[PDB]
Image (tube, coloured by chain):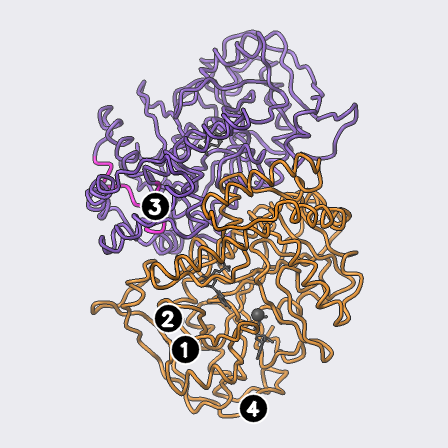
Chain colours: A purple, B orange
Amino acid sequence: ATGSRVTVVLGAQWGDEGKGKVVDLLATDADIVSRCQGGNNAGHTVVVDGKEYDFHLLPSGIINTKAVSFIGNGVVIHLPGLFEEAEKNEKKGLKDWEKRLIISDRAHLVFDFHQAVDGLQEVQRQAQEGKNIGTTKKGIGPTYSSKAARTGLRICDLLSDFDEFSARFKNLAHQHQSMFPTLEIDVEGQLKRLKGFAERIRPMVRDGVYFMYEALHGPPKKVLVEGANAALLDIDFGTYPFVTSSNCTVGGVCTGLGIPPQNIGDVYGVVKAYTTRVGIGAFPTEQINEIGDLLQNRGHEWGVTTGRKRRCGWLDLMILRYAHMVNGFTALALTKLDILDVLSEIKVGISYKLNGKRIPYFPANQEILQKVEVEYETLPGWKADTTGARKWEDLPPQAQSYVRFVENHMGVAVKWVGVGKSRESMIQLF
Amino acid sequence: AATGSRVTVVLGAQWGDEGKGKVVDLLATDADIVSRCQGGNNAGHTVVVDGKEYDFHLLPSGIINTKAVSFIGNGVVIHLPGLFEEAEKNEKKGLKDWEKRLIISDRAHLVFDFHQAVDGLQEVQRQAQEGKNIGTTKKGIGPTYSSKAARTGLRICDLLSDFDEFSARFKNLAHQHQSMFPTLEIDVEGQLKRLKGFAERIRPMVRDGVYFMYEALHGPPKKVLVEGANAALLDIDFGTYPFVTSSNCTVGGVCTGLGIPPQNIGDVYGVVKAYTTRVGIGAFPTEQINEIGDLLQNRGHEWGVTTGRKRRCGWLDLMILRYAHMVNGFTALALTKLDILDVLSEIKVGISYKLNGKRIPYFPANQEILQKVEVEYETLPGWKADTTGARKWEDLPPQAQSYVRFVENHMGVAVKWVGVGKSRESMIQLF
Ligand SMILES: O=c1[nH]cnc2c1ncn2[C@@H]1O[C@H](COP(=O)(O)O)[C@@H](O)[C@H]1O
Ligand SMILES: O=c1[nH]cnc2c1ncn2[C@@H]1O[C@H](COP(=O)(O)O)[C@@H](O)[C@H]1O
Ligand SMILES: O=c1[nH]cnc2c1ncn2[C@@H]1O[C@H](COP(=O)(O)O)[C@@H](O)[C@H]1O
Ligand SMILES: [Mg+2]
């Protein structure tokens, strides 16, 4: 009737929750593993067989040779970066990837100048207002602005008449040089490279809408959708303007792939045992102290895309319940629980107080979020190493209580618990 | 159940102007909440009840129901001057206390006057540079969504907070646009004065939309209707780019526009016009540049209600419909303007597309390919009869019923309503 329903993995915080780990796991027997929104500003690390892979644009299931990796229409692609990412992983064993990667011809293109303007605008905001967004400078925002302006160019444009394309590229090139006179654009060189890219990508392009429709209404197939960024980075629902420029929430799956809501099955909310965010913006449970350094250090909290040190803090339920209100999580994945193995006590934010009084819901004005005072509940730590745990019973009593604590306050079941970096580290609960 | 009640959605399945105002109004009669989830004030939905004819652009067409709350979601871009100007025109038509039943989400973005000016300027520029433009409605929708993506745009909540800080932000956003167009004239001070006034006037209507909708869907049972603006082929992602609007007017936009997950989406109705209309330059496979096209244009009153520009007309095109279904997953359809076909001896219908020589099983994303497609038509006999008074499926002659089935069968979606007139009573429910 409605066909197959896709399985979705979404970030429930400010990203870096370990989505690639849940996806790689769910990907072992998936037919299609796809990318939604965003671009290579996203950065995941997959650990399979004591082997580490850094992915940005490639769906994590690219490691599965029996599965087809798909990039949807909502994604913005930077060609030089795409192949750069792929080749970087070939050196690690990634083979025959081009033969199992499909790209929707409606995806927009991130050009080199889009990346430069991104940095330029950032430097501008940091020199004029003394405070910028903390973008990854990958040109994601500028690319989505062009998309909204309908001046941007897409995969299908690239594979179409090159003369027409070139003409459009040039027009788009000058426009950015108008609002940004100090922007340098080697138009001839970029076009030359792009023409080379056109042929390397031609065989991998397909009409995306038709591709997915056919996979969902033909014989049963397991389709997995990898979310990028996270709920609180969502352009609409995040801590605007300190967010990414795409919808990282469930709605983004429908708009990024061309599938209706009835073709969405399980939606997993990836929740890191503690909270982090890299970039500018309000962070209520942020711990800028000894505890903060400990989480950061033990969690190897560094952006894989930029390398910047991530800000760390306690789990925050306010943002998790908000994320759930928008995403409607069917189940949760609690990752990096082992990072807390050495804490005698573990605090978790349960509500935000403003001038001494609890606010009823997550605020739209991120500034108010800067003045709130977090109400914490202090749970007992387990002070034991859980990295070797492979089943629920291997977890000490207090670690188990922590898991249940989240499960009970969310009203959503925890299906996986991460105690390591390897695919085996995950603990399936049901 | 724990999931909550589900919302009903009405979407355009072609290139707009399908007759959505009528379907929305009909479904609103007993709706607790009627809302807009995406787009700006260029909906142009038409409602005809009790002799009166209402036009809505930014306001939900259910604003007419004094028993329901009209809601503007977070995915919407709002031009305050246009909003109240739209409300007043209708007010003088009998609409009253609308401000008392209009709720606005505090995360919705603001379309500023300079955003509108830039739309026009870029259009004039592009016009006399590439020979042709995008053909926007010049309501600043594109530039506003452009600002949203850049994260330099301002929102309702920003307008209601410290005005001084708001002012500081506005000025920066204002100057930024003056760089793109050093021809852009902006009375910064005046525009801020008018905005200060709009803020105090809109203040009592604003609320946190995410929470408001959540509560509406999880408390005592309520029926929420979602009014889609524009249409599938105008969708920023799935439409005939670049001749599209800058929002997701497809079903997903409902989730991203109101902040509700897929389990809260129920019936999704696709408004299908009995024939096809397109506005502006661009590929139109079934276009009829002849007497038949003239006939459709005249009988369907297909023309810019304001600018007066005539709309391009052609036969029904099942290729765009199936494509719109693949994206939207319609649960039922509203087949509109069947009456316009009352006089034809026969009706053609595009059933498939043929390229260089073989049929293409998909709707092309590129304008050049879509411009090259060969259309295979199916000729159906007309009913040659006035169906204006029809009110039961049994009132429609054989060839009309046959035409309704054709659409149903070829799209794979059942037809729930058949429209034969502008008025609310000019409908036929089939189930
Ligand atoms: O995957 C990610 N992990 C963490 N933060 C991210 C990720 N992608 C984007 N962001 C944040 O999103 C904001 C906007 O950056 P942009 O997406 O590069 O425009 C910044 O604060 C980034 O740090
Ligand atoms: O079934 C119908 N027959 C004829 N005209 C209709 C029908 N339904 C709606 N219309 C008209 O179609 C036009 C476009 O509708 P809109 O999509 O609400 O703007 C309006 O002028 C409506 O009054
Ligand atoms: O009257 C109309 N009916 C249907 N589509 C329209 C009309 N006017 C403009 N459009 C299309 O809508 C697109 C987006 O315009 P915008 O929503 O004003 O940004 C334009 O590029 C046109 O292709
Ligand atoms: Mg209209």
Whether marks 4 and 3 lie on the same chain: no
Specify whether residue A106 is painted magenta.
Answer: yes
> Which three-letter amino acid code belongs to the residue tagged 3?
His
Report in which chain the residue with disc 4 lies.
B
Residue A188 in the image: x percent, y percent? Answer: 22, 42
> Which three-letter amino acid code belongs to the residue tagged 1?
Gly
Q: Which residue is mark 2?
A: B284
Question: Can you see residue B236?
Answer: yes
Distance CA(mark 3)–CA(mark 2): 31 Å
Residue pictured at 67% horizontal, 56% vertical: B224
The residue mark sitting in front, 4 or 3, is 3
Question: Can you see residue A1?
Answer: no
Task: State yes or no: discs 2 and 1 in contact (Cβ < 8 Å).
Answer: yes
Distance CA(mark 2)–CA(mark 1): 8 Å
Q: Quadrant of residue B97?
A: bottom right
The residue mark sitting in front, 2 or 4, is 2
Disc nearer the start of the sequence (4/1)? 1
